[PDB]
Image 1 (cartoon, protein in one colour):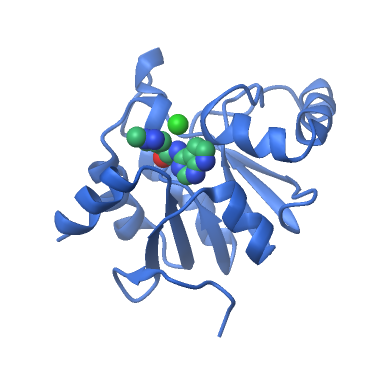
Image 2 (cartoon, helix red, strand yellow; image 1 turned 90 degrees about the vertical axis):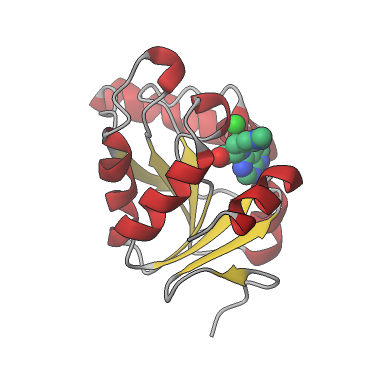
Length: 167
Ligand SMILES: Cn1cc(C[C@@H](CO)Nc2ncnc3[nH]ccc23)cn1
Ligand SMILES: [Cl-]
């Protein structure tokens, strides 16, 4: 039993809700919140910009030190950093950005990072400003993640489309 509330159950392990991931994280304080990161951990917009703003830029400060030490992530890769005031940990995961010409096949590799964590609050990878089809992202999530994932979909219209079309 966990403290996630109001989610629709899609499969044994995948749940979904129309919610602002920032507000969800502040309420639940999950062990792991997933960020829709880029390889530079530059948290400018989309989910990343919103999470970082909610940390008063502490996420960006920590991320800049991470990059200075380790260099950029790989597309499809991840790193674990602090969750600041939002969660215990933040799993920064880089899905392919279609608006940069990146290989959508890397979406499965991106979701595989979730399997290293028993429970996560997460967005749909590569959706939104990353330019991929969110229906596809949900399908890859369900077919790749085996741990317990609570998906927050900000756009209510998109949420209804995702539920109604789910196979
Ligand atoms: C129509 N539309 C698609 C998306 C993409 C989605 C991630 O896939 N973004 C977010 N998801 C959850 N919480 C969030 N907070 C801030 C952004 C955000 C947003 N709008
Ligand atoms: Cl977005």
